[PDB]
Length: 129
Image 1 (cartoon, rainbow, N blue to C red):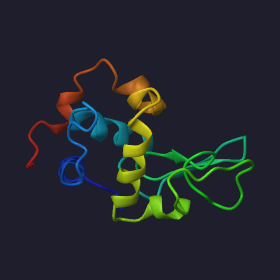
Image 2 (image 1 turned 90 degrees about the horizontal axis):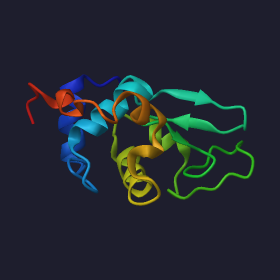
Image 3 (image 1 turned 90 degrees about the vertical axis):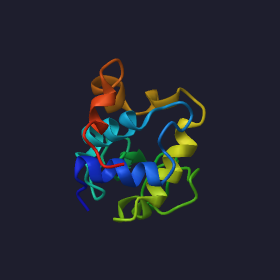
């Protein structure tokens, strides 16, 4: 599913991402925009054999199992395909585990290069939350 900007904003808030770990909803929408262009079915293979999945492009090397990633760990305890459904539950709950520690949203390269330090708040402007 390819989400509209405000449509994904409402769904994410509905899934408890607004201010999760101190990150306002704008961050998540902006991260989704640049990681997958709001497309839950986005996938990108990497040279290390891993693959990034879903709206937030979660990597299989550590968070999910796709049965072909070398030295793969499945910390979110799910098949990577679960990160591709129109139902964002899996991606959201896995992302919550990822952002909970480590380096926060700095875990998302696109968020770090296109959202961090900008009016991330703009991505929710005019939205029907």
